[PDB]
Image: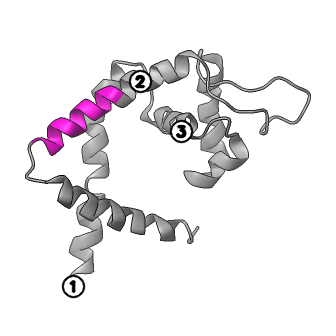
Amino acid sequence: MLSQEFFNSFITIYRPYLKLTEPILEKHNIYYGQWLILRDIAKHQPTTLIEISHRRAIEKPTARKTLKALIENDLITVENSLEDKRQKFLTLTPKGHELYEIVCLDVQKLQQAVVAKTNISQDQMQETINVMNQIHEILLKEA
């Protein structure tokens, strides 16, 4: 039908997009995996973990196995206490939003050079974010 040429036209771009975003994270010895939490963390901090499981929302296993690397690494920061520790202001670390800048900026340099080669007036760009944002409503009122 139609709908099919539709969802997979936008899905068959995920790994064709990271596959080239691999070098910029190779410039930084980092997992895209982490970055996401770090882009999830940079945007939402003081945010803590009870909320993290909420937005990207994937099982505990992967979630903390990645806050495994972030914590020792001069990366993400937690609060200090006796207090159970999901809720210890899981803020970001100093260097961390300095690691934020270059990844986020170099990734931006690529996407931009890609939009560059497209006759996509921002008019068709926004004509899209509300479709793509219109689909998060369900994967958001679905799981």
**In contact (CB < 8 Å): disc 1 and disc 2:** no
Q: For mark 3, what is the residue?
A: 43
Q: Residue at the far bottom: name it.
A: 1
**Marks 1/2: CA–CA distance:** 43 Å
Q: Which mark is residue 1?
A: 1
Mark 2 is on which residue type? Glu
Q: Tell me the residue at 48%/39% (across/down).
A: 36
Q: Earlier in the sequence, mark 2 or mark 3?
A: 3
x, y percent for residue 22 = 31, 31
Q: Which mark is residue 101?
A: 2
Q: Secondary structure at mark 2?
A: helix
Q: Secondary structure at mark 1?
A: loop
**Marks 3/1: CA–CA distance:** 39 Å
**Would you say 4 lies left or right of 100 here?**
left
x, y percent for residue 112 = 20, 38
x, y percent for residue 90 = 70, 33
Q: Earlier in the sequence, mark 1 or mark 2?
A: 1
Q: Read off the magenta span.
A: 105-116
Q: Secondary structure at mark 3?
A: helix
The quadrant the C terminus occupies is bottom right
Q: Is residue 47 visible?
A: yes
